[PDB]
Image: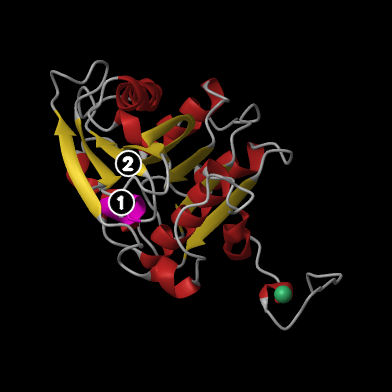
Amino acid sequence: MAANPYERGPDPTDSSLEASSGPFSVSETSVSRLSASGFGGGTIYYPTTTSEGTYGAVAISPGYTATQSSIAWLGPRLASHGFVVITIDTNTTFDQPDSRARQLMAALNYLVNRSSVRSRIDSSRLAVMGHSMGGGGTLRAAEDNPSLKAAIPLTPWHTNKNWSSVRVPTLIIGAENDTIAPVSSHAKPFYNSLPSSTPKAYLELNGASHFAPNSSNTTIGKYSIAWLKRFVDNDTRYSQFLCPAPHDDSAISEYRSTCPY
Ligand code: NA
Protein backbone atom coordinates (compact mmCIF):
# COMPACT_ATOMS: atom_id res chain seq x y z
CA MET A 1 0.00 0.00 0.00
CA ALA A 2 1.17 3.52 -0.81
CA ALA A 3 2.56 5.43 2.16
CA ASN A 4 0.10 8.25 1.41
CA PRO A 5 -3.41 6.93 2.19
CA TYR A 6 -5.10 9.66 0.10
CA GLU A 7 -3.62 8.58 -3.25
CA ARG A 8 -6.36 7.66 -5.73
CA GLY A 9 -6.09 6.39 -9.29
CA PRO A 10 -3.14 5.21 -11.37
CA ASP A 11 0.12 7.08 -11.72
CA PRO A 12 -0.56 10.23 -13.79
CA THR A 13 0.79 11.15 -17.21
CA ASP A 14 0.57 14.27 -19.34
CA SER A 15 -1.73 12.24 -21.59
CA SER A 16 -4.05 11.16 -18.79
CA LEU A 17 -4.38 14.72 -17.45
CA GLU A 18 -4.96 16.25 -20.91
CA ALA A 19 -7.68 13.70 -21.68
CA SER A 20 -11.35 14.65 -21.57
CA SER A 21 -11.95 12.27 -18.64
CA GLY A 22 -10.00 10.77 -15.79
CA PRO A 23 -10.02 7.16 -14.61
CA PHE A 24 -13.21 7.38 -12.51
CA SER A 25 -16.74 7.13 -13.88
CA VAL A 26 -18.82 10.08 -12.70
CA SER A 27 -22.35 10.31 -11.31
CA GLU A 28 -24.30 13.49 -10.67
CA THR A 29 -27.04 14.70 -8.35
CA SER A 30 -28.40 18.16 -7.58
CA VAL A 31 -29.43 20.32 -4.65
CA SER A 32 -32.25 22.81 -5.08
CA ARG A 33 -32.03 26.51 -4.31
CA LEU A 34 -34.44 25.93 -1.43
CA SER A 35 -32.47 23.05 0.10
CA ALA A 36 -29.17 24.94 -0.27
CA SER A 37 -28.78 26.91 2.95
CA GLY A 38 -26.67 29.97 2.20
CA PHE A 39 -26.27 29.52 -1.57
CA GLY A 40 -28.36 29.14 -4.70
CA GLY A 41 -28.23 25.40 -5.25
CA GLY A 42 -25.84 23.39 -7.33
CA THR A 43 -24.98 20.22 -9.19
CA ILE A 44 -22.80 17.66 -7.42
CA TYR A 45 -20.46 15.50 -9.52
CA TYR A 46 -18.90 12.53 -7.77
CA PRO A 47 -16.97 9.34 -8.55
CA THR A 48 -19.41 6.46 -8.67
CA THR A 49 -16.90 4.15 -7.05
CA THR A 50 -16.04 4.25 -3.35
CA SER A 51 -13.68 1.25 -3.36
CA GLU A 52 -10.44 3.24 -2.96
CA GLY A 53 -11.67 5.40 -0.07
CA THR A 54 -13.24 8.79 0.43
CA TYR A 55 -12.34 11.84 -1.65
CA GLY A 56 -11.65 15.49 -1.12
CA ALA A 57 -14.38 17.95 -2.07
CA VAL A 58 -14.32 21.11 -4.18
CA ALA A 59 -16.84 23.95 -4.45
CA ILE A 60 -16.80 26.07 -7.62
CA SER A 61 -18.41 29.50 -8.04
CA PRO A 62 -19.39 31.24 -11.30
CA GLY A 63 -18.90 34.94 -11.89
CA TYR A 64 -21.00 38.09 -12.17
CA THR A 65 -24.31 37.61 -14.04
CA ALA A 66 -23.45 33.94 -14.63
CA THR A 67 -24.88 30.58 -13.57
CA GLN A 68 -23.67 27.01 -13.25
CA SER A 69 -23.70 26.45 -17.00
CA SER A 70 -20.62 28.68 -17.30
CA ILE A 71 -18.56 26.35 -15.07
CA ALA A 72 -20.36 23.05 -15.66
CA TRP A 73 -17.60 21.35 -17.64
CA LEU A 74 -15.29 21.42 -14.60
CA GLY A 75 -17.62 19.11 -12.68
CA PRO A 76 -17.09 15.94 -14.70
CA ARG A 77 -13.53 16.88 -15.63
CA LEU A 78 -12.32 17.16 -12.03
CA ALA A 79 -14.61 14.56 -10.45
CA SER A 80 -13.37 11.94 -12.92
CA HIS A 81 -9.90 12.18 -11.33
CA GLY A 82 -11.22 11.47 -7.83
CA PHE A 83 -13.00 14.46 -6.29
CA VAL A 84 -16.51 15.40 -5.20
CA VAL A 85 -17.31 18.67 -6.96
CA ILE A 86 -20.24 21.06 -6.53
CA THR A 87 -20.83 23.75 -9.14
CA ILE A 88 -23.00 26.28 -7.34
CA ASP A 89 -25.44 28.97 -8.31
CA THR A 90 -25.26 32.06 -6.13
CA ASN A 91 -28.14 33.62 -4.21
CA THR A 92 -28.33 36.23 -6.97
CA THR A 93 -26.30 36.57 -10.15
CA PHE A 94 -25.23 40.06 -9.00
CA ASP A 95 -23.56 38.89 -5.76
CA GLN A 96 -20.14 40.47 -5.15
CA PRO A 97 -16.90 38.54 -4.55
CA ASP A 98 -16.97 38.54 -0.74
CA SER A 99 -20.56 37.27 -0.82
CA ARG A 100 -19.52 34.47 -3.18
CA ALA A 101 -16.77 33.54 -0.71
CA ARG A 102 -19.37 32.90 1.99
CA GLN A 103 -21.47 30.86 -0.44
CA LEU A 104 -18.53 28.67 -1.41
CA MET A 105 -18.07 27.81 2.26
CA ALA A 106 -21.81 27.25 2.73
CA ALA A 107 -21.72 24.83 -0.21
CA LEU A 108 -18.84 22.89 1.36
CA ASN A 109 -20.76 22.79 4.65
CA TYR A 110 -23.77 21.35 2.82
CA LEU A 111 -21.65 18.73 1.05
CA VAL A 112 -19.93 17.53 4.23
CA ASN A 113 -22.95 17.57 6.53
CA ARG A 114 -26.20 17.20 4.58
CA SER A 115 -25.69 16.01 0.99
CA SER A 116 -26.62 12.52 -0.18
CA VAL A 117 -22.93 11.95 -1.05
CA ARG A 118 -21.46 13.16 2.26
CA SER A 119 -20.29 9.61 3.02
CA ARG A 120 -17.91 9.78 0.03
CA ILE A 121 -16.14 12.91 1.32
CA ASP A 122 -13.20 13.32 3.67
CA SER A 123 -14.34 16.48 5.43
CA SER A 124 -10.76 17.38 6.39
CA ARG A 125 -9.75 17.85 2.71
CA LEU A 126 -11.65 20.67 1.01
CA ALA A 127 -10.93 23.18 -1.74
CA VAL A 128 -12.47 26.20 -3.47
CA MET A 129 -12.42 27.35 -7.10
CA GLY A 130 -14.25 30.01 -9.06
CA HIS A 131 -14.41 32.12 -12.18
CA SER A 132 -14.10 35.91 -12.31
CA MET A 133 -15.89 37.37 -9.28
CA GLY A 134 -16.07 33.73 -8.21
CA GLY A 135 -12.29 33.71 -8.36
CA GLY A 136 -12.22 36.78 -6.17
CA GLY A 137 -14.50 34.92 -3.79
CA THR A 138 -12.05 32.01 -3.92
CA LEU A 139 -9.24 34.27 -2.70
CA ARG A 140 -11.40 35.66 0.10
CA ALA A 141 -12.56 32.18 1.12
CA ALA A 142 -8.92 31.08 1.24
CA GLU A 143 -7.96 34.10 3.35
CA ASP A 144 -10.77 33.55 5.87
CA ASN A 145 -10.59 29.72 6.04
CA PRO A 146 -6.94 28.66 6.35
CA SER A 147 -7.92 25.00 6.91
CA LEU A 148 -8.77 24.76 3.20
CA LYS A 149 -6.31 22.54 1.35
CA ALA A 150 -6.27 24.39 -1.99
CA ALA A 151 -7.70 27.37 -3.88
CA ILE A 152 -7.83 27.92 -7.64
CA PRO A 153 -8.98 31.39 -8.78
CA LEU A 154 -9.77 31.37 -12.52
CA THR A 155 -9.35 34.75 -14.29
CA PRO A 156 -10.20 36.33 -10.93
CA TRP A 157 -11.79 39.74 -10.37
CA HIS A 158 -11.62 41.59 -7.05
CA THR A 159 -11.22 45.17 -5.87
CA ASN A 160 -8.91 44.02 -3.05
CA LYS A 161 -5.40 43.51 -4.45
CA ASN A 162 -3.67 42.49 -1.19
CA TRP A 163 -3.87 38.77 -0.34
CA SER A 164 -0.74 38.66 1.81
CA SER A 165 -2.51 36.69 4.57
CA VAL A 166 -3.45 33.72 2.35
CA ARG A 167 -1.92 30.52 3.77
CA VAL A 168 -3.78 28.07 1.49
CA PRO A 169 -1.94 26.68 -1.58
CA THR A 170 -3.21 28.85 -4.42
CA LEU A 171 -2.99 28.46 -8.19
CA ILE A 172 -4.11 31.58 -10.07
CA ILE A 173 -4.96 31.14 -13.75
CA GLY A 174 -4.94 34.31 -15.82
CA ALA A 175 -5.87 35.01 -19.45
CA GLU A 176 -3.23 36.95 -21.36
CA ASN A 177 -5.72 39.06 -23.35
CA ASP A 178 -8.32 39.45 -20.58
CA THR A 179 -10.07 42.82 -20.87
CA ILE A 180 -12.63 42.21 -18.09
CA ALA A 181 -10.23 41.31 -15.26
CA PRO A 182 -6.92 42.38 -16.85
CA VAL A 183 -4.07 40.33 -15.44
CA SER A 184 -2.02 43.51 -14.90
CA SER A 185 -4.62 44.83 -12.43
CA HIS A 186 -6.14 41.60 -11.04
CA ALA A 187 -4.48 38.18 -11.39
CA LYS A 188 -0.86 39.34 -11.25
CA PRO A 189 -1.25 41.79 -8.33
CA PHE A 190 -3.08 38.98 -6.52
CA TYR A 191 -0.27 36.49 -7.17
CA ASN A 192 2.49 38.96 -6.26
CA SER A 193 0.84 39.74 -2.91
CA LEU A 194 0.57 36.08 -1.89
CA PRO A 195 3.30 35.15 0.63
CA SER A 196 6.27 33.29 -0.83
CA SER A 197 5.94 30.90 2.14
CA THR A 198 2.54 29.76 0.81
CA PRO A 199 2.75 27.19 -2.03
CA LYS A 200 1.59 29.10 -5.08
CA ALA A 201 1.65 29.34 -8.85
CA TYR A 202 0.58 31.73 -11.59
CA LEU A 203 -0.41 30.22 -14.95
CA GLU A 204 -1.20 32.57 -17.83
CA LEU A 205 -3.13 31.27 -20.83
CA ASN A 206 -1.55 32.40 -24.09
CA GLY A 207 -3.87 34.53 -26.21
CA ALA A 208 -6.87 33.84 -24.00
CA SER A 209 -9.94 35.93 -23.19
CA HIS A 210 -11.80 36.28 -19.88
CA PHE A 211 -14.15 33.49 -20.99
CA ALA A 212 -11.54 30.79 -21.57
CA PRO A 213 -12.61 29.13 -18.27
CA ASN A 214 -16.23 28.77 -19.48
CA SER A 215 -15.43 26.16 -22.17
CA SER A 216 -13.52 22.88 -22.02
CA ASN A 217 -9.84 23.83 -21.81
CA THR A 218 -7.08 21.23 -21.78
CA THR A 219 -4.62 23.48 -19.93
CA ILE A 220 -7.01 24.60 -17.19
CA GLY A 221 -8.07 21.00 -16.61
CA LYS A 222 -4.54 19.61 -16.53
CA TYR A 223 -3.10 22.07 -14.02
CA SER A 224 -6.26 22.32 -11.92
CA ILE A 225 -6.24 18.54 -11.52
CA ALA A 226 -2.53 18.51 -10.66
CA TRP A 227 -2.98 21.29 -8.11
CA LEU A 228 -5.92 19.63 -6.37
CA LYS A 229 -4.16 16.26 -6.38
CA ARG A 230 -0.95 17.69 -4.96
CA PHE A 231 -2.56 19.68 -2.16
CA VAL A 232 -5.99 18.20 -1.45
CA ASP A 233 -4.61 14.62 -1.62
CA ASN A 234 -0.99 15.45 -0.64
CA ASP A 235 -0.28 13.46 -3.81
CA THR A 236 3.35 14.10 -4.73
CA ARG A 237 3.01 12.03 -7.91
CA TYR A 238 1.62 15.31 -9.33
CA SER A 239 4.60 17.48 -8.37
CA GLN A 240 6.17 16.53 -11.71
CA PHE A 241 3.57 18.60 -13.58
CA LEU A 242 3.77 21.64 -11.30
CA CYS A 243 7.57 21.59 -10.85
CA PRO A 244 8.95 19.74 -13.88
CA ALA A 245 12.61 18.74 -13.89
CA PRO A 246 14.86 16.37 -15.86
CA HIS A 247 14.81 13.88 -12.97
CA ASP A 248 11.17 13.16 -13.90
CA ASP A 249 12.83 11.04 -16.62
CA SER A 250 13.16 7.45 -15.42
CA ALA A 251 16.71 7.40 -16.85
CA ILE A 252 17.83 10.28 -14.59
CA SER A 253 18.12 9.57 -10.87
CA GLU A 254 19.19 13.13 -9.93
CA TYR A 255 19.41 16.50 -11.65
CA ARG A 256 20.79 19.72 -10.16
CA SER A 257 21.46 23.02 -11.89
CA THR A 258 21.76 26.78 -11.56
CA CYS A 259 18.62 27.22 -13.69
CA PRO A 260 17.10 29.37 -15.01
CA TYR A 261 19.41 30.13 -17.93
NA1 NA B 1 14.14 9.93 -12.50
Q: Badge 1 is on which residue?
A: 74
Residue range (magenta) = 76-80
Q: Position of residue 85 (x, y in %)?
A: 32, 41
Q: Position of residue 37 (x, y in %)?
A: 24, 16
- x 36%, y 52%: residue: 78
Q: Position of residue 113 (x, y in %)?
A: 33, 20
Main SS of residues in magenta: helix
Is there any visible trace of residue 258 in the rendered image? yes
* Real-space Cα separation, disc 2 to disc 1, in angstroms: 8 Å
- x 27%, y 53%: residue: 76
In the drawing, does residue 65 fall left or right of residue 203? left
Front disc: 2 or 1: 2
**In the rendered structure, which amino acid carries the disc numbered 2?**
Val
Q: Position of residue 226 (x, y in %)?
A: 51, 56
Q: Is 185 contained in the magenta span?
A: no
- Circle 1: is it few (<14), some (14-19), or many (20+) Cα within 10 Å? many
Is there any visible trace of residue 177 in the rendered image? no
Q: Badge 2 is on which residue?
A: 85
Give the farthest residue toward the bottom: 251
Instruction: Give the colour scheme shown.
Output: secondary structure
Q: Quadrant of residue 137?
A: top left
**Residue 32 vertical placement versus 249 (above, below):** above
